[PDB]
Image (cartoon, rainbow, N blue to C red):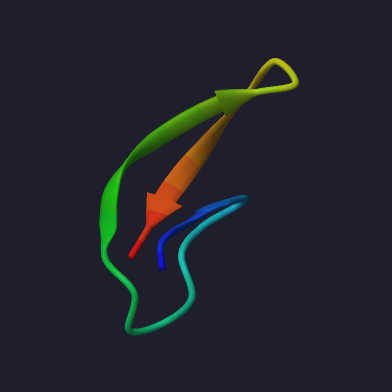
Length: 30
């Protein structure tokens, strides 16, 4: 699956987009 993450994706994951949640920008990580 993919996961909204902050501050960044786990090494090896790809930032495939972004999430907006609780007033912050998250990386959408696949």
